[PDB]
Image (cartoon, rainbow, N blue to C red; front, side, top):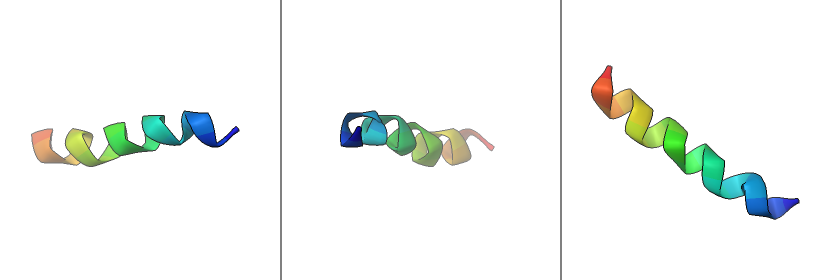
Length: 18
């Protein structure tokens, strides 16, 4: 299910907030 791979990207923008 490589489609869920897009969710990983959300982890990069989340660090920008912290």
